[PDB]
Structures are given as structure tokens and as C-alpha cells.
Image (cartoon, coloured by chain):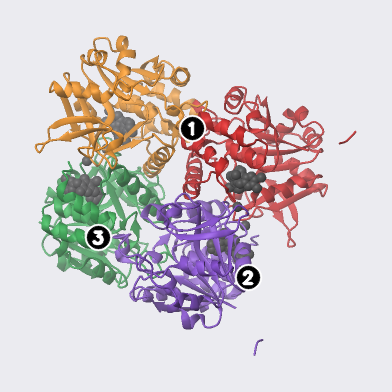
Chain colours: A purple, B red, C green, D orange
Amino acid sequence: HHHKRKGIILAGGSGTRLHPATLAISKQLLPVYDKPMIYYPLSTLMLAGIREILIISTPQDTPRFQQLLGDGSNWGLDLQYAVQPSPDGLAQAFLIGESFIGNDLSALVLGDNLYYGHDFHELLGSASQRQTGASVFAYHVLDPERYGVVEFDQGGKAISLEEKPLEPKSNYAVTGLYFYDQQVVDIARDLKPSPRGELEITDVNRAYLERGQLSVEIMGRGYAWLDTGTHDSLLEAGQFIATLENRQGLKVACPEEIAYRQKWIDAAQLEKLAAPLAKNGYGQYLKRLLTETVY
Amino acid sequence: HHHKRKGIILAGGSGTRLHPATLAISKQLLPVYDKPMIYYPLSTLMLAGIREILIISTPQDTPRFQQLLGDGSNWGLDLQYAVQPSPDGLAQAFLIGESFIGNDLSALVLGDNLYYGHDFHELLGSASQRQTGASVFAYHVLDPERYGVVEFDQGGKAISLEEKPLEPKSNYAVTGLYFYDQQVVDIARDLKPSPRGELEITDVNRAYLERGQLSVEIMGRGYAWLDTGTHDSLLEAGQFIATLENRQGLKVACPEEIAYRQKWIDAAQLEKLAAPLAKNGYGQYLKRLLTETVY
Amino acid sequence: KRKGIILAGGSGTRLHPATLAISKQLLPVYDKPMIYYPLSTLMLAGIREILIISTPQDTPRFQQLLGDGSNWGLDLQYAVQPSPDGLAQAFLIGESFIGNDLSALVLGDNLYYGHDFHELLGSASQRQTGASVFAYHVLDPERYGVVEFDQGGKAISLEEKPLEPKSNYAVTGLYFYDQQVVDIARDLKPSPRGELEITDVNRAYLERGQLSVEIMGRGYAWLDTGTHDSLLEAGQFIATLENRQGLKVACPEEIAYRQKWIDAAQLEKLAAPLAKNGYGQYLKRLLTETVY
Amino acid sequence: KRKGIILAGGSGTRLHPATLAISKQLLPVYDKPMIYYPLSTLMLAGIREILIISTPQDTPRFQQLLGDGSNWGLDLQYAVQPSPDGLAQAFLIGESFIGNDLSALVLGDNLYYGHDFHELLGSASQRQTGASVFAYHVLDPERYGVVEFDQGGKAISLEEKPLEPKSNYAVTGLYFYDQQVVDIARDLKPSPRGELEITDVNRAYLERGQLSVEIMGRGYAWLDTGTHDSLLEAGQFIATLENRQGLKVACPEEIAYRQKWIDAAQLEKLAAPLAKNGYGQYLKRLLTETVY
Ligand SMILES: Cc1cc(Cn2c(N)c(N(C)S(=O)(=O)c3ccccc3)c(=O)[nH]c2=O)ccc1Br
Ligand SMILES: Cc1cc(Cn2c(N)c(N(C)S(=O)(=O)c3ccccc3)c(=O)[nH]c2=O)ccc1Br
Ligand SMILES: Cc1cc(Cn2c(N)c(N(C)S(=O)(=O)c3ccccc3)c(=O)[nH]c2=O)ccc1Br
Ligand SMILES: Cc1cc(Cn2c(N)c(N(C)S(=O)(=O)c3ccccc3)c(=O)[nH]c2=O)ccc1Br
Ligand SMILES: [Cl-]
Ligand SMILES: [Cl-]
Ligand SMILES: [Cl-]
Ligand SMILES: [Cl-]
């Protein structure tokens, strides 16, 4: 009898690549300017209207995310948690997240991706509304070799996907934000590991492409999709957010704000979250959101 | 007998505020990352479909802008030039630009304002399409005291404008990009100087407001409106553009690109502009635009 | 001999939510945890025996990061400061650690850089009586302990965060002390603000005419990591220097190796688990390259 | 006595369109034109008599900025380099300016910062025979003149932009010369690349055993302003230092005042037209404040 879309954030082991900074704490707990990196994809899923979210991290890191975020109920969310013992590729998320997904639609977001721009809400909404097939976003980059790359024909139809090609067919990278129908778990179960031993998200997306069920929306150049892959790019992302926030006196990817604007929490709930933070600019910001109209 | 909108860039004296950097060359000739500051508002007017543009600068600086930009015909534009002897306020632009405006619609842009974001073309187009009255944009800022400030009532109607108020009524600044009908010159002619001796753009905009002819569109938080008022903010703006451009391998506010995408110049014309620039990344970029599809 | 204290104290809620569930002095400045910077500073002054004082929450996190220090030729101990009751409390908490030895205190969020910094530390630590501090010209002296000089350059007053500062010389977060400091700290009354003040310890030395105040020149960088904006500035400053030089600032393994506290075999062992990133590659490179 | 040359040469089209109709070495690094930095460097080495060599297009722009230098206690002259035919051409163009005196050359886009920089310049300029250069450890030595040292630290080879560099020590864009340099430059054949190379002048001194190569230590900042990305890094580096200290790096008026080339009356006159911004306020402040 009938009378919905779940989220997954993959916040896994960045191995030893960013050591020694990441000896102290996992990558997606490092801040970008003023807030932990995971706040950014979490906020992204929230902006897409997703409230029920599974956070996949290492056994070691699970407790630390849990300590930061809890069960989400203060922000009107239902956050759950699962361990990824080993870094065996991004598609593993769907096998780990299998019982969490159930028979629902899903969205996957990488824990180290930051997005910003105008009408991002509307760009997400058109992905999450398409209730069959899958939807991904293509973004023009300088270094497409580092990503899944999309080739378009002359009428703008997607015709191939390639994982980290040495000779990319275009400058269009697939961003680390994906929307899936109920077929994803069964596609993911049939994947054989790749040459380097990972369950690849590109192979999942190619299965949808081969069935004619993949929507590739362009994420325009007027959106910022930022890179937290290196210490240098983590620093750029910090500068970028700081510049915007200090210009505007508005925050990017403040989860409490997003829950309040989605009406998942009300003004009294937002005031209670502001109380313990009253003595810093972040809690003062939440307080200011109770009385200021922001368009 | 019948069978159009002109642009003005006010690139005037920043006095001695940014000295000694500006002893060598005027403010709007200083670069923001890789291109002279004036490229940014020029590109903004171009994106609005404006081809016929008057550049107002000091007698000293006029020749230097002229040397940089010429008459615009290489980029499919008709740039003209006029001197502002003295820094007597922004509204003077309409008296200086009087014969240039003629009986047409106009757009005014400050030579030190940078804008960026998604569907900026569409945001401009809806201003320039409204062929009577005036249109301005409101942008949430931290420091509204430095700008013209807009007060909205509870239904979102603009009800007051104030120039640099010590006690701002909102955090909404009027950005330095304005669209005017044929009434602007006559409003500007009736302005008495303000307490500090300037012909104020806020007084022009209030005249439209009092006639019920001012449209105030919100420029959303997903747009970046950057500040080149200080050495620090000029540096932020540099970092901001560099981060975006190096992420994307695409340029922000490249005039040649904008003229090519407006179809004001064709592929052969763009190739000829790329030739003298062939030995640097900027000319290599223009060359790459001849063969790459960018969405 | 001289023992060191790093005060990696509580920043309260000021850097929340970055610091929710994540210790301030474990936040990275560019590529390495904040605490590497004061640690390296102490190590550069020749100090191997170091006490890390932090919150009840954060102390075990530093322990789990750094252990007893033996891998870098150090002797690290740990103590907790229950409550942010003033910087001078370090000497009470740290009484039995200091014992009857000379000491140096460094603040956990203070970053230093410059030419002959080794020698500037050397000259302070060699002075075996009195106390030694550094005065650095700053834009906002009101945020710090301020030093007033007379026309002949003698220090004549110290004030903690004065509303009307007598100079632009701030006392940096690096202090050297003789065997008197514990008893000076023990006889302190808390200030109006409710803190055992480090400036109050330093004035006590000044009143005895036993405070050396040396100028840390304008060619040195003393950076603060109090706020999100300063932490960011500091990252960009270090990254700019490191990417230019292909050398690191405040890499403890390098400093221990250069002090001869660890040898080439042990440096090589430290490089192995970091081999697949640039930090281990740098440690490996330091075995074969002559760096003047 | 020692005369100076600033080579503010042609960067071609590489920084276009920023440099279209606007001279490279007049682009600002943070708050001041690029050329203030090498000028100040020369001024810090005690050199008052300075030749600015630039393009036919840019030379009069520097002239119109700086004039004869008399307002800062300097003696500035100007010469043109018709074509970017190598850095060593400075000595041919500058032959009659150098006369029979000692010289120093500095590259117009080179920025230096650090403790006791004054003394490092002092020691090079005091050496009245041979030539003196500085070797600075860098990440990308292939972009520079590279110095090879033997196991005892003696310089044994110099190579201009080697595809396989023998070390990570780059020769900085600051060179001190005796009365031989003009005749060495005059006897140079152009390289395969079509340039009169400064490394070729320096090897000629090395071959005579008259090249001093001193290490510019890792505590000094030597920044390059070749590209848009480096020019930006340099701005952020200087701004971070200046906003922290409330002191300026490479403010020529301050350096002339501190060298006693201009007095307090003249510094005050220079402050007046800049009074309404921070730069003049700083100059005014330097009349009453003691800065160590
Ligand atoms: C429509 C709508 C607007 C907003 C306003 N908003 C926006 N636009 C943003 N952005 C600037 S965003 O859409 O680009 C964005 C949202 C979440 C995470 C990253 C970026 C934000 O960070 N926070 C925020 O409250 C929030 C919720 C909803 Br529903
Ligand atoms: C529709 C359209 C898109 C573009 C693409 N484009 C965009 N979007 C941008 N932007 C990132 S922008 O719309 O925010 C912008 C344009 C001009 C000046 C500043 C920002 C740009 O700088 N250059 C550019 O070619 C150009 C012309 C036209 Br008409
Ligand atoms: C003399 C000496 C030099 C060095 C080299 N060195 C230097 N100079 C530095 N500096 C750039 S520093 O002296 O300004 C510095 C040292 C420790 C912590 C911060 C800065 C460094 O960070 N690491 C380093 O190995 C190490 C130990 C000793 Br003893
Ligand atoms: C000893 C001395 C110190 C000073 C102080 N000083 C210093 N140290 C600096 N430096 C920070 S510097 O020596 O590293 C430097 C000098 C000139 C150009 C670049 C950096 C400066 O920029 N300006 C300045 O007035 C001036 C003249 C003389 Br002689
Ligand atoms: Cl876009
Ligand atoms: Cl928006
Ligand atoms: Cl110094
Ligand atoms: Cl050094």
C-alpha cells in the first residue's frame, strides 16, 4: 500500500596522502575556513531536500563524525552511520548502504566536495525530481584527467564516460554528487573491481548510460565546484569561502540555516542551537537569522 | 520614423586613497589577477548586450584607457570616451554623457565593480528588457554603511534608499550597476549637490522610486559581488578570480570571449586577436575557444 | 639544563564549529598540525624535555598523536589544565615537571619564522638567571602584553591588554625562566579578569630588574593563530615559503635530525610510512641533500 | 663607492593583458609599485646613485613616477634597453654610468625580506674585489642560474637553466661587481638562446676564483614576480607581514629617512600629499615613533 530519496555521504580514508595534517583527524573533519569539511556536502544534500542520510567513514573516524553531528535530530535530520573497513572504491557505498537504501531512491555525495552558486537549489531539485534513472553533473575543469570525464556528441548528448583517462575526450568532469533510482544497488552488486582494484562509480554511471537512463546536466561555469584534494587546494577553498562570507555577512553551507529555511526546524529550535554558540560569530549569526529577512 | 541601450563605465579618479600603487596608473587600470580591472565591468555591460559604451575618466587617464581598449571595433563594440575634470559625484556621468545618451536608454556601471555567477546573463537581461523606469540590484553585505542601502517593507517592496547611512535600515546594498530609461538625464539635471558636494546616484534612484518607477531586483547570495575599494580587497578579488580560472580552465570576464559568444565577432576575427597573444596563456585560451564547445 | 612547556589551552567556543570535537592546536597550518610549530620552536632552542599542557578533552588527543616523543629524540610528558584560568597556571600544573630546572614556555598557537632564529633563542636560553622575553612591533598592541621603553631602550612597564597601550611592542608567546618562576606564580593573586596572568609573572621579574626584553626584529615573522582569518593567513604564509624553497618550516623530524637527536637510520624509518606523500619524500630527500 | 642598476626589462607579452599599455614593474605588489622593492633593496645596501634600465616604452613611465630621486635623497638616472637581449647588456648600456666605480645589479621583479638583510648586503658591498652573489635553496632550480657546490661548500659550476640541475641552489637576482664587469660583458659572445647571460659574467669571475657565493638562508624570503600567480602570492605575503606588524616592507621614504639621506622636515613634506591615506599616515607616524 502507498500513501522519497535518501542520502549517502562517503567520508572515507584519504590514506596517508595529506599527512601529517590528517594524522590528528580525518580529512572530512578538517575545517574549510570556519566549519568542518563535512558541513559542505551535508548542506548540499539538505538543499536537495534530503533528510535521511548515511555517513560512511572508517571504523576509527565513525565516532568522531558521530560526536560532531549526532543523529541529526537537532537539525531535523535522521543521520545514520556505517563503517567502511577498507578504501575499495566509491561504488562500495551502495553495498555498505544497501539496507539503508532499501527500496528508495538515493543520492551520493563525496565528503570533500564543495559547491557554491546561484539557484543551486533549483539545479539539485531538477536532479532529485527525475524519479527514474540516474542524474549526474558535468563541470568544465582544467585537469579532467583527475576525474570521471564525459564525452558529448555535437547535439550535446552524453556518449561516453571514462575514469581518469590519461587522454581525456573533453574538459567535462563528472562532479562527486550523484542521484540514483532503485536500480543502483543491483548494478553495484554486479561490478567487478577495476584494474587498480576499486569498485568504480564511473562503471555504475556507464550502466545507466548504456540503458539510456543517465541524465548529464551541465553545472555551469557560474558555479564554483572546489577541490579539497591537496593542502594547496584545501587552502584555496578556505580563502574562497572566507571572501564570500566576509563580503556578504552570510554563511555558505551553514546546516542550521538550511534546516531553518527548509522549515525542518522552527525559530525556537534555531534559538536553542544558537545559545551554546552565543559567544562566537557563528552562534551570533544563527541568532541574527531569527530576526533578519534574507532573500 | 521608427524601424536600444547605451552603456557608461565611470572609471574616475580614486584620488590618493590607494597611493602609492595608483601614482603609476589609475585604479581601473590595475589588474585583478590577469586582466585590467576595467575588463570586468566592460564584460558586464557586454553580457547585457550593450555594444555602444562611453568611458568616463580623468583627462590624464583617458589616453591610457584609449591605448588599452581603442574604439572597441576589434571586439564588435563602439567605445567612446569623455573626460571628468573633477570627482563631483557619480550622477555627473549623465551630464557628461548627455549627448552620448541622446534619446536612448542607458546603463551605468562603476569601473571597479566585479560580478560573478550563474545566469548572470539572465539577471542582466531582465533589467535591460524593462524599457521604462529604472532597475537596480540589491545585494546582502556585511558593511552596508559604505553603500546606497535599500529598505524593503514586509511584502518585499522597496520603500527607502539612503546614501551611506551611519545606521543602515537593512544589509542590502545597491550594487554599482544601474539601468535607466530616457528620464535619467532630466532627473540628473535637477540634482543639487549633497552635503559633501557630490551629485549622488542615490538621489537619481530615489526620484525613480518616488514616481513608482524603480525596480529593485535581488542579486542573490549565490552571486559574488566583489569589492576593489582597498588594497586588501583588491587582493581578495585577485585570489577569487585566480581560484575560479585555475579550477575551470575558463576565464571570467574575457571580453573577446564575450563578443564571440554574443556573435559580435566571428571565428576568423577571434583568431586574429589570438595571434599577437599566442605566446601567453591568454592568447592560447582564445585559440582554444575556436575549437572547444563550452556550455 | 632547560625544560619546556607548550600551553595548548582551551579556546572555549570561539572557533566553533571547526573546533567541535577537534582540538584547536591539532588544526593544520598548511600541511602540518598547529602544535608542530611551537614544538619545533622549543626543539630549535635545544629543548628536548617538554610538557604539553592542554584541556581534559584535548590532552589525550595530543598523546595519541605524539606519544612520548622517543621517535624524534624527545622526552614528552602531558598534563591537564581543568579550566582556562590563565597562562601562569602552567607553572603550578607544571611544578613537579620543572623541578629545580630552568624552563621555557611557549603558546600552542604561536608561529615564528626567520633568519638566525636559532641564535635569538640560543641567546635567551644561555642566560641562566632572570627571565627572557621578546618584544615584537605590532598593529594592534591592545590584544597583548605591551612593553613600554624609556628613551634609552630599557623596559619600564608591562601591561596586559591595555585600553591605551604605551607602545606598539607586544610581548611574544615565548618565555624563558630561571628557578624563581614557580614561587612567583604560586604567590600570584588572580587579576580582575579572573586569570593568573603571564604578564604578572613577567612584571615580577621586571620589578626585580631581572627581565631581559629583546627585540624580535621586523625581519622575523611572528604569526598568531587565534581566529579563522589568522589561521588562514598563516597557512598561506607557510605554503608560499615552502613551495618557493622546496624546504619546510617547523618540520620536527628535520629539526631533531639537524640537532643530532635522531640519526639517518631513524629518520629513514620515519620517512617510510609517509613515503607515498610529499612529507615522507621530503624526509627521504633530507638524507642525501646538503642544505645550508 | 658603489653605483646600482635596476634592470626593469621587457616581459614581452607574457603578462598580457595586464601589461598592455602598463609597465610590468609598475604593477603593484600589495600597496606599492613593484619597483619600490628592488629600489629599497639597493637603498638598504647603502647605494644612492642608481640607473633604471627599462624598455623604450616603459623608461619614461619610471621617469615620470620617480624623477631624479632627489626627494628621497637619491641620484636616479635612466637608460633604455631597445631589445630584451640578455641581462648582461645592463653593463654595456650602463658602461658610462658605472664609469670606473664598483657596481650592484638588481632585477626589477625581485623581492627580498628578512632579518639582518642589511648586514648580508653590507658584507657583499664591502668586498671591493671580485663579485658577490647569493645562492638560495628553491623547488624549481631549472628556471634559474644554478650553483654546484663541492663537499667542502665551494662553488664549482654555474649553469643557466639546466635541464638537469646539479643542485637546488638558485643564484638570486642581486649581484655585486668590481671594475672588471664592463670588460667581461664586452667580451661576451651571445648564448645559443640569443642572450648576453648574467651567468656567463658570473662564471667568468668564478673561473678567475673571484666569485663569492654566499648562502641566502631559508629564513630569508626571496620572492619572484614573474607570473600572475607569483605576483599574487607576493602581495599576500607582504600584506600579511604589514597588517601584522603595522610596519612596511620596502617603503623607500622610510629607508632614506633611516639612512639619514632625508631628514624629518623632508619626510614630513613627503607625508603631506599622502596624508589622507594610510601610506602618508605611516610616514607621519615614523617622525614620532621609535622603531627598533
Ligand atoms: C531556497 C533556499 C535558499 C537558501 C539560501 N542559502 C543558499 N543559497 C546557500 N548557498 C550560497 S548555496 O545554494 O550555493 C549552497 C547551499 C548548501 C551548500 C552549499 C552551497 C547557502 O549556503 N545557504 C543558504 O541558506 C537556503 C535554503 C533554501 Br530551501
Ligand atoms: C550566455 C552567455 C554565456 C557566456 C559565458 N560566460 C560566462 N558565463 C561568464 N561568467 C562567469 S559571468 O556571466 O558571471 C560574467 C560575465 C561577464 C563579466 C563578469 C562575469 C564569463 O565571464 N564569460 C563567459 O563567456 C558568455 C556570453 C553569453 Br551571451
Ligand atoms: C641552525 C639550525 C637550522 C635548522 C634549519 N631549519 C630552519 N632554519 C627553519 N626555519 C625556517 S626557522 O629557524 O625560522 C624555524 C625553526 C623552528 C620552528 C619554526 C621556524 C626551520 O623551520 N627548519 C629547519 O630545519 C635546523 C636546526 C638548527 Br639547530
Ligand atoms: C638597518 C636598517 C633597518 C631598516 C628597517 N627596515 C627593514 N628592516 C625592512 N625590512 C623588513 S628588510 O631589511 O628585510 C628589507 C629592506 C629593503 C627592501 C626589502 C626588505 C624594511 O623593509 N624597511 C625598513 O625600514 C632600514 C634601514 C636600515 Br640601514
Ligand atoms: Cl553558469
Ligand atoms: Cl542566489
Ligand atoms: Cl630584523
Ligand atoms: Cl636563515
Tag 2 subunit:
A
In the picture as drawn, the residue positioned furthest to the right comes out as B1
Residue C274 - label: 3
> Tag 3: residue type?
Leu
- Identify the element where label 1 is drawn: loop
| Quarter holding residue C73 | bottom left
Q: CA distance from mark 2 to mark 1?
A: 45 Å
Residue, disc 2: A130
* 3D distance between C-alphas at marks 3 and 1: 42 Å
B258 left or right of B3 in image: left
Give B160 or A219, whichever is nearer the viewer.
A219
Residue shown at 72%/47% (left/top)? B125
For residue B278, the mark is 1
Question: What amino acid is at disc 1?
Answer: Ala
In front: label 3 or label 1: 1
Quarter of the image with the N terminus of chain C is bottom left
> From the viewer's perspective, is the residue at label 2 or at label 3 nearer?
2
Residue A22 percent coordinates (x, y): 32, 63
Figure quadrant, ligand 1 = bottom right
**Disc 1: CA contacts within 10 A as few (<14), some (14-19) or many (>=20):** some
